[PDB]
Image (tube, helix red, strand yellow):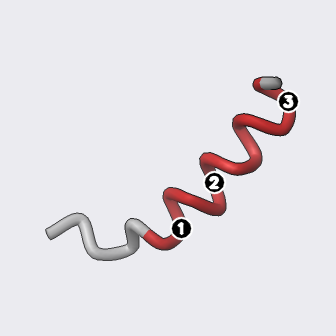
Amino acid sequence: GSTLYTESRKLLRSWHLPSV
């Protein structure tokens, strides 16, 4: 669910730290 999906995106996108 987006609600939780979006939150996860923030966390996930957090790791992606290195956009390299």
Q: Amino acid at mark 2?
A: Lys
In the rendered image, the residue lying farthest to the top is 1
SS class, disc 1: helix
User: Nearer the N terminus, badge 2 or badge 3?
Assistant: 3
SS class, disc 3: helix
CA gap, disc 2 and disc 3:
11 Å
Which residue position is annotated with label 1?
14
Q: Amino acid at mark 1?
A: Ser
- Where is residue 12 shown, x and y percent of the image? 56, 59
Q: Is residue 15 above or below residue 12?
A: below
- Where is residue 15 shown, x and y percent of the image? 48, 72
Q: Is residue 6 above or below residue 10?
A: above
Query: What's the residue at 84%, 38% (across, down)?
Result: 4
**Which quadrant would residue 10 be assigned to in this image?**
bottom right
In the picture, the quarter occupied by the C terminus is bottom left
User: Nearer the N terminus, badge 1 or badge 3?
Assistant: 3
Label 1 crowd bin: few (<14), some (14–19), many (20+), radius 10 Å: few
SS class, disc 2: helix
CA gap, disc 1 and disc 3:
17 Å
Query: What's the residue at 77%, 25% (across, down)?
Result: 2
- Where is residue 6 shown, x and y percent of the image? 71, 37
Which residue position is annotated with label 2?
10
Label 3 crowd bin: few (<14), some (14–19), many (20+), radius 10 Å: few
Q: Amino acid at mark 3?
A: Thr
> What label does residue 5 carry, if any?
none
Which residue position is annotated with label 3?
3
CA gap, disc 1 and disc 2:
6 Å
In the depicted view, which residue is nearer to us: 14 or 1? 1
Please report contact status of discs 1 and 2: CB closer than 8 Å, yes or no.
yes
Give the mark count. 3
In the rendered image, the residue lying farthest to the front is 1
Query: What's the residue at 39%, 73% (across, down)?
Result: 17
